RNA sequence: GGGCAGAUUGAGCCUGGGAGCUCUCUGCCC
């Protein structure tokens, strides 16, 4: 902990199909 | 598609200072 240079995770994201 | 939670003892980026961003996997919810 006590650090930076990251964000909250995701479920899924966009794609071509 | 999106949110919330878990993997940075998963990958990448910019920056002096992220309540930061891109990218992937899993669970729950819409």
Image (cartoon, helix red, strand yellow):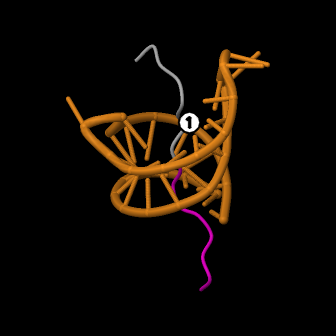
Up/down of B27 relative to A15, above or below: above
Q: Position of residue B26 (x, y in %)?
A: 34, 58
Which residue: 62% across, 70% down? A14
Residue A5 in the image: state x and y as whole percent. Answer: 54, 30
Task: Give yes or no for residue A9 being in the magenta stretch.
Answer: no
Report how many numbered discs are placed on residues in the image. Answer: 1
Q: Nearer the viewer, residue A11 or A16?
A: A16
Q: Main secondary structure of the magenta part?
A: loop
Nearer to me, B26 or A7: A7
Of residues B3 and A14, which is closer to you in this image? A14
Q: Residue B14: x percent and y percent? A: 66, 39
- For label 1, the SS is loop
Query: What residue is drawn where x is 60% and y is 76%?
Result: A15
Q: Chain of mark 1?
A: A
Q: Position of residue B23 (x, y in %)?
A: 53, 61
- Classify the position of the C terminus of chain A by image quarter: bottom right
What residue does disc 1 label?
A: A7
Which of the 4 image quadrants contains residue B3? Answer: top right
Graded by Cα atoms within 10 Å as few (under 14), some (14 to 19) or many (20 or more), the crowding at tag 1 reads few
Q: Where are the magenta residues, as a range?
A: A10-17
């Amino acid at each position: 902990g006590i650090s930076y240079g990251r964000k909250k995770r995701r479920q899924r994201r966009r794609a071509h199909q």
